[PDB]
Image 1 (cartoon, rainbow over the protein chains, first blue to last red):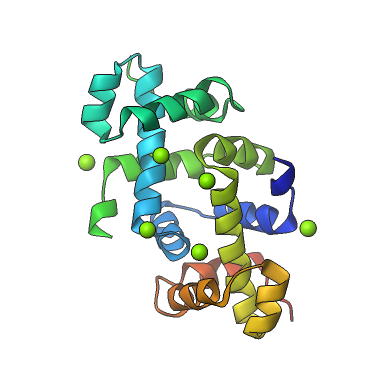
Image 2 (cartoon, helix red, strand yellow; image 1 turned 60 degrees about the vertical axis):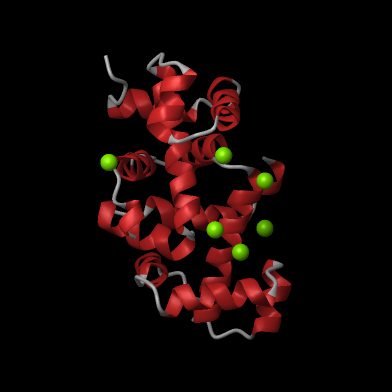
Length: 97
Length: 97
Ligand SMILES: [Mg+2]
Ligand SMILES: [Mg+2]
Ligand SMILES: [Mg+2]
Ligand SMILES: [Mg+2]
Ligand SMILES: [Mg+2]
Ligand SMILES: [Mg+2]
């Protein structure tokens, strides 16, 4: 966290928060990231959602491709982090009821 | 690009575009990414800005820490990409005049 209190980090975030729609998101993240990086963040995000949907590690590994080690890492951030995943899931009504 | 046309990628982007302020950005990206990943994206973004500000590779390597190989990679995405960096720089009035 301390290493992230930088004006560089803050401008990255303003850049990210200025994106207006998914086509802009695609353009930007594809400029800044590799395909695999984007695929890697989307996998973590899906693991996290499925974890809160109460799915098993097997079902998560199947559906997402994540190894169980990845699943376990995400699970640490989900549970012992800033509660960012959860606040998005609540806000966007994402969790399969 | 083709590998990124996924519902998983689309939900990551909706999650990212729902973030309302920098504190939310910090909470979310810190949950989803490692410190080094965030530092790595903010470095690329700063390299890209300084490149469009017409600074030399030496000055960019000094100010940002990027190796010149990183600078050269960013420069490919800046110039031969989706024009996402440039559209953010224009929109946010970021380039030092
Ligand atoms: Mg600073
Ligand atoms: Mg790669
Ligand atoms: Mg991982
Ligand atoms: Mg799909
Ligand atoms: Mg790391
Ligand atoms: Mg790099």
